[PDB]
Amino acid sequence: ARCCLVMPVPPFACVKFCS
């Protein structure tokens, strides 16, 4: 899938993945 909403704070990873 593709990142839907990434967080600028650590973890900088994505919070919600878009299907």
Image (tube, helix red, strand yellow):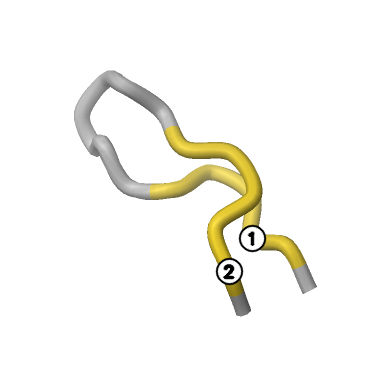
Residue at the far bottom in the pictured view:
1
In three-dimensional space, the C-alpha distance between marks 2 and 1, rounded to whole angstroms, equals 6 Å
Picture coordinates of residue 13, whole percent (x, y): 32, 47
Looking at the picture, which amino acid does disc 2 mark?
A: Arg
| Residue at left offset 46%, top offset 37% | 6
Picture coordinates of residue 19, whole percent (x, y): 79, 74
Q: Is residue 5 above or below residue 1?
A: above
| Residue at left offset 64%, top offset 49% | 4
Asked if residue 18 lies left or right of residue 6, the reply is right
**Which quadrant is home to the N terminus?**
bottom right
N-term mark: 2 or 1: 2
| Residue at left offset 55%, top offset 57% | 3
Residue wearing tag 1: 17
Picture coordinates of residue 5, whole percent (x, y): 59, 39
Q: Are marks 2 and 1 in contact (CB under 8 Å)?
A: yes
Looking at the picture, which amino acid does disc 1 mark?
A: Phe
Q: Mark 1 packing: few (<14 Cα in 10 Å), some, or many (20+)?
A: few
Q: Is residue 2 above or below residue 15?
A: below
Q: Is residue 13 above or below residue 6?
A: below
Q: Is residue 10 above or below residue 5?
A: above
Q: Mark 2 packing: few (<14 Cα in 10 Å), some, or many (20+)?
A: few
| Residue at left offset 73%, top offset 62% | 18
Residue at the far right in the pictured view:
19
In this rendering, which labeled residue sits more in front, label 2 or label 1? 2
Disc 2 is placed on an element classified as strand
Identify the disc placed on residue 2. Answer: 2
Disc 1 is placed on an element classified as strand
Q: Nearer the viewer, residue 5 or 11?
A: 5
Q: Quadrant of residue 10?
A: top left
